[PDB]
Image (cartoon, coloured by chain):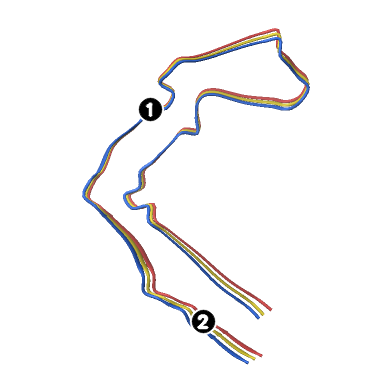
Chain colours: A red, B yellow, C blue
Amino acid sequence: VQIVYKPVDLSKVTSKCGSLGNIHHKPGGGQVEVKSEKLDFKDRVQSKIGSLDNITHVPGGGNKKIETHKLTF
Amino acid sequence: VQIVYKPVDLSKVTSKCGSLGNIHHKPGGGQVEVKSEKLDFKDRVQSKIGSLDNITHVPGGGNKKIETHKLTF
Amino acid sequence: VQIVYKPVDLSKVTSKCGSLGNIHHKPGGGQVEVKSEKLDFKDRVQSKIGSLDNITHVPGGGNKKIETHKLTF
């Protein structure tokens, strides 16, 4: 038995952008009010209140190549 | 048995953009109000209130190539 | 037995754009109010209130090429 696993990759993933800007992300400009009375809890509580984990992601590229090679015998 | 696994790739994934911008994302500009009275929780509680996990994602390319090669004998 | 697995790819996935912009996303501009009185929860609880998980995705390309090569003997 002979196996010759010989894939050839000459690909490209490319971008050109002339200018990139004037990006505004303003999450949670509005008021938040939370009121609690006579609450009972008897197992774990997780609470997040306000502006949390908001992302502004502005790469000049952001291009991806994902390549997977597998052989099983 | 002979196997010659010889795929060849000269592909391109390409973008050209002249300008990218004037992007406005404003989650949660409105008021949020939560009032809780006499509530009873006998198991785990998770709570999120306000403006959370919002994304502005503005890549100058954002092009993707996904390429899987598999052999099983 | 001989197998010669030799696919050849010279394909292009291409985009050209003059300008990309003036994009406005304003989720949750309206008021949210949540009164809650005498509720019993004998069970796990998850709650989300306000403006969550909103996305403004604005790639200058955003082109995709997905490619799978498979051989089973």
Q: Is residue A22 left or right of residue A36?
A: left
Q: Quickly name the residue at label 1.
A: C26
Q: Whole-Å distance between the Cαs marked 2 and 1?
A: 51 Å
Q: Residue at x 66, y 81 (%)?
A: C73
Q: Is residue A51 above or below residue B6?
A: above
- State which chain disc 1 sits on: C
Instruction: Give yes or no for contact between labels 2 and 1 (Cβ–Cβ under 8 Å).
Output: no
| Quarter where residue A15 is shown | bottom left
Q: Is residue C16 above or below residue A47?
A: below
What's the residue type where badge 1 is placed?
Lys
Work out which quarter of the rendered image holds the N terminus of chain A and state it. bottom right
Q: Is residue A25 visible?
A: no
Q: Residue at x 51, y 81 (%)?
A: A6
Q: Is residue C10 left or right of residue A73?
A: left
Mark 2 or mark 1, which is nearer to you? Answer: 1
| Quarter where residue C43 is shown | top right
Q: Nearer the viewer, residue A54 or B36?
A: B36
x, y percentage for residue C19? 22, 46
Q: Secondary structure at mark 1?
A: loop
Q: Quickly name the residue at label 2.
A: A6
